[PDB]
Length: 230
Length: 230
Image 1 (cartoon, each protein chain N blue to C red):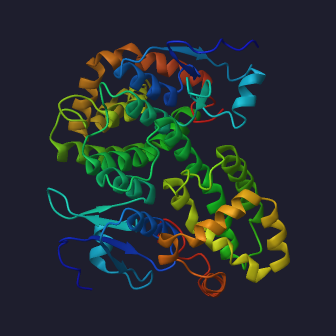
Image 2: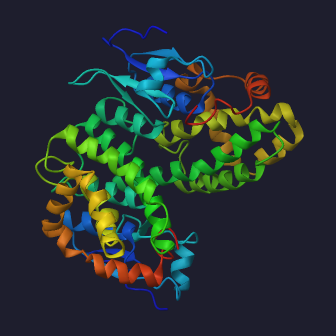
Image 3: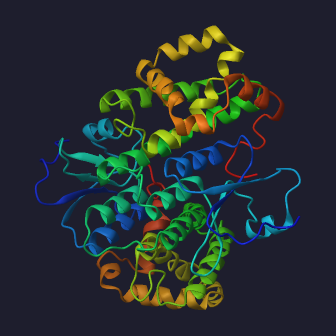
């Protein structure tokens, strides 16, 4: 009910627990080693001052200091790109504008996997598997074409972290149908390999949950708080 | 049926005549003073080699030289941002990452005006006026808050040109209902003023059509070739 104080030395993320768009921003902040605090939003009991600054209830929100005072920044892509431009250390986007443009196109393409996953977790993991699979074929071919351990090269870059939150959630499906999951996984050998490597990343590990934890969460909550708005 | 030759000194835009997403890219290319040629696409009689390189038939397409050969670049936002990064002269985005993030948020917000305009030109200018008006209120307030002649400051910037193609098309509505148009216009005095100033811009003038020309075009063609895909 009472808002937090004015920002000092840390950036502030307003985030709904288990929201993948917030997970995205958490990964980038950590990768860029920027100090931040998380203000946990309750999707039900939402503060009036928050709605007032965010009438469409978009999530997550990164609050930053500016010349004219503390400001809300919206939309996970815009937020993460802001962070990559503002803070010059530990750059995540490619230095090559062509490669970066391709990375941006792939982020947009990934939205089809997001849509399918959203419907899936909303309907006891019964539907939209096909959207997942089709998108995974594109990313398998793309990773193979690049011939690096990650989309970013020898180390994870912006595309890797942008895509990860949904990929990490997919592992919950092994709790639903173990055998059907492993078969599906085998279709994308380089992507699967990349998944394993991403799981070992210190930044990933900081904000990770297990297959079981995601499974117990999504069965009860479904997708009510999974979108880019509440 | 026969594709154009390999690129040399000019970039190549594949563009459907009167398509506002292509109009966007034409404005930026001109603003950045980059040499280019336009390959006019017939939405009906489409070349097989084009479909093959672009199976979802996205428009426009900017073909560019790369280290590995000539490549298609898709999506007008990605295309224009590529151009602004690749070519360092005549920069269009703000140097301030916060201001640029706001500009990106406004481009996304503008999609609501695009949707309304799309439906409008598709249905003999009878529907979706309300989406237009609501978006115009946001941009009026934003331009007022900035207190400059343009969204980019003293001169037009990326946001100005990104938004212009749809704004220029709106003037056709004065051919439909003169009196209802002028009243609606008077609601947004700073935006209207900006519109007048944009019309005098040398870059705008290069790729402009009149209210009547848009009106005669849209009545016959409707919105069939107006989207970001064919």
